[PDB]
Image (cartoon, coloured by chain):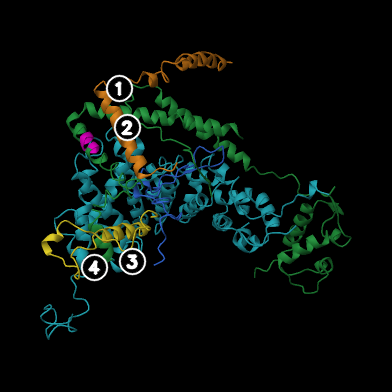
Amino acid sequence: NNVTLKNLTAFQLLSQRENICELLNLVESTERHNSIINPERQRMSLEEMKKMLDALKN
Amino acid sequence: NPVPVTYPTDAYIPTYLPDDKVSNLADLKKLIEMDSRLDLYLTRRRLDTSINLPTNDGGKVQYSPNLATLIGMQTGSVNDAVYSIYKYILINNLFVTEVKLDSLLQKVLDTNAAHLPLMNVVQTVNKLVDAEDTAKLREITKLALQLNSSAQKYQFFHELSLHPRETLTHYLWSSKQNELVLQGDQYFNEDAARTSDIYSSLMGNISLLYSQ
Amino acid sequence: TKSIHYSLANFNVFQSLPKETARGVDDLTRMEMALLSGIPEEIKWSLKKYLTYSNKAPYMISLRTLPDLLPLFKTFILPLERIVEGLNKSSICDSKAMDSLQMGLNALLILRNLAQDTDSVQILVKDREIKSFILFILKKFQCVATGDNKWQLYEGNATFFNELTHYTLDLMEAISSYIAPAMKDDHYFQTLVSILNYTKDRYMVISILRSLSRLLVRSKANEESAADNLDHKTLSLIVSFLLLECDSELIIASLDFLYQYILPGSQRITELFKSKECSLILEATLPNLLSYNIATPDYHLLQKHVKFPQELSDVSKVACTFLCLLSNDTDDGAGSAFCQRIRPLVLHKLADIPPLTLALSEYMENT
Amino acid sequence: INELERLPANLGTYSLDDCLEFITKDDLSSRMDTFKIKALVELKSLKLLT
Amino acid sequence: SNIPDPTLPPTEMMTRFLHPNWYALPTTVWLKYGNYNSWAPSFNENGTVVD
């Protein structure tokens, strides 16, 4: 916790610039997308549903 | 009163994403409502009521031969003693509602006042004888905020597609109005506040102060 | 020093004759006159001092004492009905939009403060232009609560939005007392019943339960009324707050709301007990609510080798009055079958807590 | 402070502009105490730092 | 005049010093309701800055 006016105003600018500098295609953020979709959590979770759905049939 | 914590407990799980592009969000809403109904049935059975000792080592007490006439038993827990004494005060309709003491109560209490509060009555009665769920609730509330972040970035870029002229001028004004806020506290840093470089509005201020 | 040639400030006719208040306009008239002048950067000071006098001396700027104040504040309140109409796209785009939004939120919080003392709320309910604005804000927040696609929040503006609801809701707490509904389909009740199911914050939940409780007094339960818009989906939630044994504010608000919902007639009781997920809660919570934070006799001698309680908490008092009113329902309504299914459990709470026998008098005389 | 609190208390200044006032041996030359004031100022201003 | 000379150890310009940009701001507090409650509010917002 312990947020202040400076810590908040400098967070709004960081969020606005992360988006603006991405519209101009100046930012490469592949080491952040390789934490959601690209990791095996997209496949291994499906490999857990593929067995929980079958365990739920008996 | 509930104790305040230092980490977010829940998240709103936003609903401004188009419900024809992202699917199974309604599945998530149904699962969350079902878990919200799967614990309202547990908390209820945590306050469960049970009637297991109306009449039925320090749990067993030997009653005096005097109190054995208002109970029907000579031994039993203290709960049975206080309960059966109250039942005797209730059956004989002794409470003043128009406790008025009976005749046998005179002996069992060794008191001739014939009128005594119930508090004193039970006073004489005594005178005669779990961790993993926190981690799960922090892991889930650590994903509904990542979802609440990606949804905000989608909301921004989608509101940038529509009306880009309106969003860009807002971004340029937020930038020209936030880079000024962050550059307002760089004047007091203890290595530029004793070198006499900033003392040559820090001059009208001393006018207001001296007048104050 | 004191001479005519040194300075001409006291010749013979003004050195002690000027009044003690001859130094300009008074601090109140200065606020009132600098509030209708069109210059910005000046309204931001008047609406700062009015905002101060609404938390340190509200009895000085009361609406009744100055019958020319609401005309001024509405000039800053009404433009919010247009600004709030935006806030789904980028509606703030310069330094003159925020200057007109903060000058409005200040004028709204000032009314929220002046709407807490009595004989000052008696002026907002007379002017329909404020009740309409409150209804508009409640409508927008209902659109945010429901999730429809007609109006989206554009989360980047939530900072300016979540500070309007927590003021209009507080304007409704003082207004819901002065009104009593008489029609089924009626705003100010469908919005609150929709927000309560979503708000997910304690302050709003309590403010809504208090507003709903105050929107059911001075009414009879023998005909159509606002009490028919809620169903077994909202009443299955207000009574669920009784299960929350971690606080003494949601339980009191829920018991107070049920006590206000039951008061008129006996059909309300028959309706409340229709469901089989609301009677099972009251049946297994109202006994335990008569010994909530009451320091039970602590029977622990069954594993070792009494000091019975003397007073009772506020929750036990409210649950006692609740069972008192539920006691005298009828000889056939569910209000009596409930008090009969609770007797073998209220008896233990009467045996372990003495002072209930005086408070549960009416409940015992009816069984 | 050490190097300044050891200077002669009778410090004066002979300047190259006193010729134009024709100071005699029995009169007081103007601007006689110039480095004395410039030393007292640097001393008292170092004692008045806090 | 009993003004401390600069050799003494009072001398330092800012040891404890807070700027309004460093003031703590009111924010949403989070509440905990047992461990089997999913209908509890779990928030408390009184008009905070982020809110």
Q: Position of residue B103 (x, y in %)?
A: 81, 69
Q: Secondary structure at mark 1?
A: loop
In the figure, the cyan chain has which letter? C
Q: Amino acid at mark 3?
A: Ala
Looking at the rendering, in which quadrant would you find the N terminus of chain D? bottom left
Q: Colour of chain E?
A: blue
Tell me the number on the disc at residue A15: 2
Q: Residues within 10 Å of mark 2 (few under 14, many from 20)?
A: few
Work out whether B151 lies above or below B92. above
Q: Chain of mark 4?
A: C
Q: Dots 3 and 1: beta carbons under 8 Å?
A: no
Q: Colour of chain D?
A: yellow
Q: Which mark is on residue C57?
A: 3
Q: Quote the CA–CA distance across marks 4 and 1.
A: 55 Å
Residue type at mark 4 is: Asp
Q: Of the residues tagged 4 and 3, which is closer to the observer? A: 4
Q: Give the image quarter of residue C41.
A: bottom left
Chain to which the residue tagged by mark 2 belongs: A
Neighbour tally class for label 1: few under 14, some 14-19, many 20 plus, Cα within 10 Å: few
Chain drawn in green: B
Q: What is the CA distance from the residue labelled 3 to the residue labelled 1?
A: 54 Å
B203 or B191, which lies in front?
B191
The residue where tag 4 is placed is: C27
Q: Nearer the viewer, mark 3 or mark 2?
A: 2
Q: Residue at x 56, y 41 (%)?
A: E34
- Give the magenta part as a residue range: B170-175
